Amino acid sequence: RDPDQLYSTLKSILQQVKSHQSAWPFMEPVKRTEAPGYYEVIRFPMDLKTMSERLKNRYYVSKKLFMADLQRVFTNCKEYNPPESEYYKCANILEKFFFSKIKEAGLID
Ligand SMILES: NC1CCN(C(=O)C2CC2)CC1
Image 1 (cartoon, protein in one colour):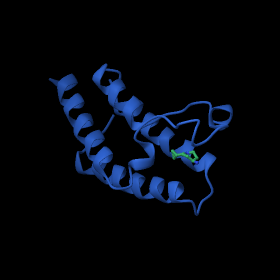
Image 2 (cartoon, helix red, strand yellow):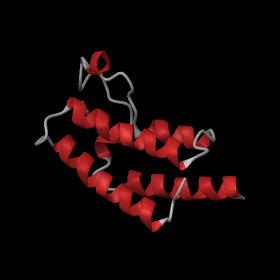
Image 3 (cartoon, protein in one colour):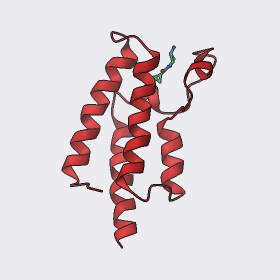
Image 4 (cartoon, protein in one colour):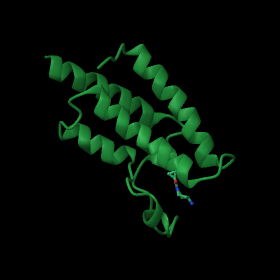
């Protein structure tokens, strides 16, 4: 299936992203205990667990929707954290890896 093909390819890309050694900050929703005013500042939180559930719920009917959610993980991180923080550094490493996986899979809209 074109729908099941898309699902299979996204599932593979998302699982590879999640397994990456730089993914650890992004694995689950940001915890207030670690960032008490986070949710006062970041209006569209996103994380890889939430993406995994969205994928399982057949939300990602296009490349565009999947890219927007992963890209939001990164933009939240860079909005919130200084550039020389480990979080920012992880974001840019994981983004490079993400793009290489999108390209390796031939994913197009
Ligand atoms: N003290 C940190 C805790 C984790 N935060 C994040 O932005 C991580 C990257 C997702 C908020 C600030």
